[PDB]
Length: 303
Ligand SMILES: NC(=O)c1ccc[n+]([C@@H]2O[C@H](COP(=O)(O)O)[C@@H](O)[C@H]2O)c1
Ligand code: NA
Ligand code: NA
Image (cartoon, rainbow, N blue to C red; front, side, top):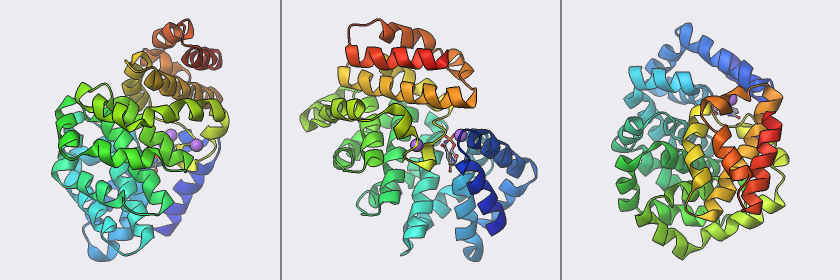
């Protein structure tokens, strides 16, 4: 339905308030039975794209759980269908859906891979469309954060690091940023560390974080103007104490950006719940000047 699709997009677009408005509208879609209807219509050829178009915008934390419990196979399939359509409007929708389905759990990451979702993302990594590539880089970051060790062998077998490096060197800041985040998360796997160190992608972090204001970057893309979920950030906390100094810097930069976003929402309480305060205080007093200043700024913004 075009009217609901426009309501939710307009809601997400509201600076500051959009997080709470979109959250509520997406919960309403589930409670009214609309989400179940979308999932049933996403296998009907005439209704697939319109259904997928709306699904891509409503895969919040609680709706991701609903999809996993009631019809993951159907939603993964419509996403794959969209990546094989000649229209770039479709490819963006399909990769966007897959991007969000990688933000639920280790087991769900395994099922999405099993059903071909990762194959579709990697296929689209060879496109030139910026929006699609942004979805791809974000999807691989999410998979790196949520996949767990059980999915790290599969990424190695499929040479996911190889696919990430060209995205890390992309000139677009959003493609580069989330490709680097995925790399910074994957270097915790020593098998992947050697390939990362060989690539030199981690050398891109220091120029980026020192040349980008966290707040301004938070406004660079409507798709992430409200930051990430608490469960996404919970999984990023371990990178604040990563082996690689470059990874700690990027994680510290991100939490500084998120602190500013959550401050303007009034949601700084999430950092205490995910046990990020003590991790940030640890960084705020460490000798790493770059990560230390970002972590200190974050704590001030949390208040
Ligand atoms: N997090 C944001 O800044 C933002 C902005 C616009 C839409 N959305 C929608 O939210 C869902 C993803 O939820 P999270 O961003 O909370 O992980 C997707 O359906 C996406 O289209 C998120
Ligand atoms: Na949000
Ligand atoms: Na943004």
